[PDB]
Length: 218
Length: 218
Image (spheres, rainbow over the protein chains, first blue to last red):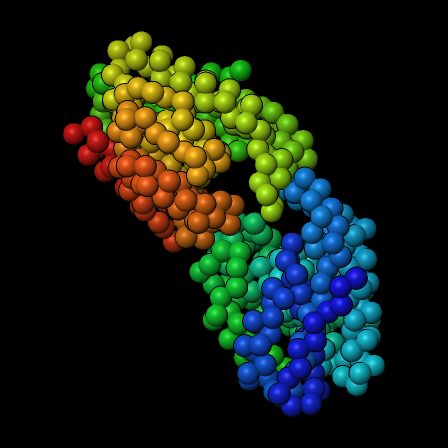
């Protein structure tokens, strides 16, 4: 286990975003983003975990950081559900590790990009039974959501922000919109934002995440 | 071993475009495209081959029309050179078949989308040592180009049009750009054209392909 990066904010922290990267990236991949946001969010810690290094099937069993195995791209994205739930258990330990440092669970947010986003959806709306600031889901999808999904009263009150490219060829705009629709139909305050890009992060998309966090925190 | 689609022009054919599909699609995928072009290109025949149905590793062995196997995506790509060559040798046979009907080589074009385009680069600029009207590459790249690429004087005379989406997440714009730069560095007449799309084909792109074709056969 590589330890997560902890980027300290300008003032003493009273909120926290835990941010998961996508397939094959490391804890640093989102450092420049966490830093852009800490320019306006003066009391919000960013905790950047790193996925276990493990074999990824679609990549010839190449070992690389990965939240769960992907075993097929087409026609059905076939994944390790067992590896996802472990990652999800990891993130829940993190939330608890952050509460112990004195951050109120209502001011902890989960963010995820791509493969990381799928672990953030499972954590907040399947595993987590407490307060929570928010979920921020970036160019992603919830492989573990389904018509049988049911949300407890607590999970219902976690706000979510779902962002996606129009031209994303890896995670289809629809797959990301299908996770947004699951939550919308179940009474979850949820926002949808699209941007003219592919499977990437844009400067304006980061501005909007800042605006959205600053609204939840104030 | 399915047979090619053959779309006869409005007037007696004196030209030909062999147009290959991408992974998982069939010979019918570009039939609407060929049809559109023929309404402007009155003596151009289009033969649309379909790739042999094979296990694909990155899709879990799922059997589907495939020009060559893809074994890994990241971070070192891996393809089957064996299957690429049999695809390439089958393309050549189709060129020799068109010649045999009474089309001049220099009026025959190769065109390819995604996986289809990698085979078409390889056939033109590595295998084929004779006259050829040109190569049209959509959303693709050259897996077999490298630092050691050297072209024959006749390979150098084959014109090319390379087209790409700015937001392609399956084959990066940068991977297409590199096929372009290898062709331009070796004295090939290449044209590059980018579009604000992903891994797909736009109306405006097909428009451009036609006007390129019109110029070439004028």
